[PDB]
Amino acid sequence: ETRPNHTIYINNLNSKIKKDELKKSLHAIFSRFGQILDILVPRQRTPRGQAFVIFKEVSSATNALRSMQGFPFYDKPMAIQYAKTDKRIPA
RNA sequence: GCAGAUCUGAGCCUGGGAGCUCUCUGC
Image (cartoon, rainbow, N blue to C red; front, side, top):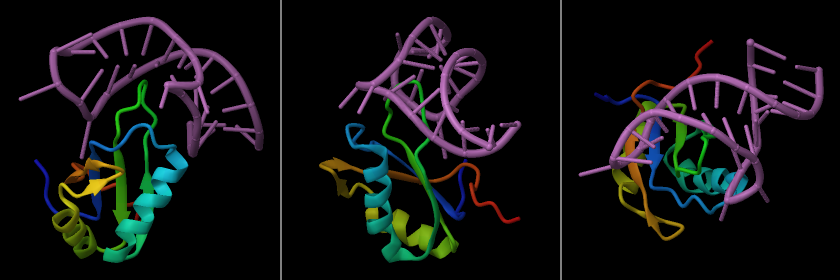
């Protein structure tokens, strides 16, 4: 169960890409949709090609999810969903 | 505790990967 929120969850990412470059590249491509609060690439026991992009506005997440769904990124089609739980930290 | 680290540290769980623990580093 997911519903629109600030955070998109991306997998099927190319796991050979260095994490720093991956973050820069995700930021460059997804910043077009709106301001990004953070990009998380969680460390796991093995590389699994997963990341979260946290937008400042939900509409940005909505349009990013629609527009980039299945779009090639480093030669792999992105699989995007809304995050099950918003990663936004509104403190 | 917080933040980081493995196709370039490790053991598990899973067996169609949005899982757990450890170790190391800084604070």
